[PDB]
Image (cartoon, rainbow, N blue to C red):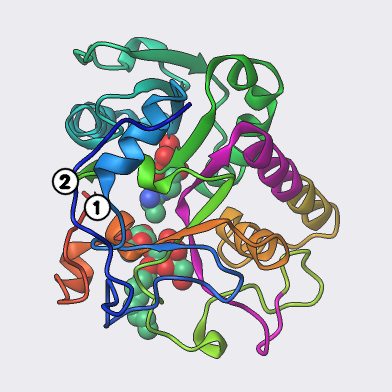
Amino acid sequence: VSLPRMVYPQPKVLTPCRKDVLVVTPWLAPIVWEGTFNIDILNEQFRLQNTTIGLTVFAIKKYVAFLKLFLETAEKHFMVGHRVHYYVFTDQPAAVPRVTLGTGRQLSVLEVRAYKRWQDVSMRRMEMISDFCERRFLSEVDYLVCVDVDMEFRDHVGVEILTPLFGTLHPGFYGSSREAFTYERRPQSQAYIPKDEGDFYYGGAFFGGSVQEVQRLTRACHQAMMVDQANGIEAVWHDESHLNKYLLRHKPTKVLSPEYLWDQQLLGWPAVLRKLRFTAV
Ligand SMILES: CCCCCCCCO[C@@H]1O[C@H](CO)[C@H](O)[C@H](O)[C@H]1O[C@@H]1O[C@@H](C)[C@@H](O)[C@@H](O)[C@@H]1O
Ligand SMILES: C[C@@H](N)C(=O)NC[C@H]1O[C@@H](n2ccc(=O)[nH]c2=O)[C@H](O)[C@@H]1O
């Protein structure tokens, strides 16, 4: 489908968008910062495909308390103007708040078991996401965005993130050397990465992609976790450790800056962050 005529500022070849940060990876994946994209062009591209975005969130046991603000703020900031399908995974279907949705946006509640240990609640998201890719997501959305629930949207999160596979730079480590990254360092674990390997430390709280690529990632991580379990070992940062191993070996096609995953209480508001889009409560 052809784009219509649009009037916007000419991109200048001899003026970089950002002089302060890396905006492309060494494997030529964009790193998404404010100033790198014209959202008007991207909106047109994705609307012409009638794109549908799925957003998964787990609200198990006491984490149902976070849904109201998560969902209300998503309505303000997440893919506004596009088709969105929220998928709320919960052990308490009656506890999901009744949030008023904009046109072209729907919510489905998916009842799942609650594990006793929070580590397992966190980890088993991979199995559950993969199982639901297997039928539901394949037919209903084009992309899946998988996030933590104890968060709020404060600024635009849109189609600029969409790509076959993305990860997000963890806010605690975007300035760190790879030696300092908290990857799993025990060779006995499937998540093992040595001190001399690694591109970035990706956050387990924000990843996604096409349904096919997310199904692959989540299936791979769940299987790695099952091998670790049979061997009596649990990765240092659980699902996030396996995510990082996956993304080292299967490079993402975009990387999101820490604009997309932030904690203002712990880290302030650095000058390199022009927007805080999705933040810890
Ligand atoms: C020298 C650097 C010193 C600075 C360290 C700041 C980042 C620490 O971050 C924790 O990082 C862990 C991995 O190593 C896990 O991803 C954990 O979930 C995360 O805490 C989460 O995310 C955080 C951002 C906070 O919201 C915290 O409350 C969460 O539990
Ligand atoms: C680090 C921070 N986002 C966190 O506390 N947990 C990761 C997520 O896993 C899910 N979780 C975890 C423990 C729990 O008892 N319930 C739950 O839904 C929530 O979606 C959480 O956001």
**Residue 239 x, y percent position in the rendering:** 59, 53
Q: Residues within 10 Å of mark 2 (few under 14, many from 20)?
A: some
Q: Which stretch is magenta?
A: 193-222
Single out the mark in the foreground, 2 or 1: 2
Q: Is mark 2 within 8 Å of ligand 1?
A: no
- For ligand 2, the image quadrant comes to top left
Q: Are marks 2 and 1 in contact (CB under 8 Å)?
A: yes
Residue beneath the point at 61% across and 32% down: 211
Q: How many marks?
A: 2
Q: Nearer the viewer, residue 50 or 137?
A: 50
Q: List the residue tagged with mark 1.
A: 279
The type of residue carrying mark 2 is Arg
Magenta segment includes 211: yes
Q: Report whether residue 158 is seen.
A: no
The type of residue carrying mark 1 is Thr
**Residue 241 x, y percent position in the rendering:** 61, 63
Seen from this angle, which residue lies furthest front?
Answer: 5
Q: List the residue tagged with mark 2.
A: 154
Question: Which of marks 1 and 2 precedes in the sequence?
Answer: 2
Residue beneath the point at 56% across and 89% down: 179
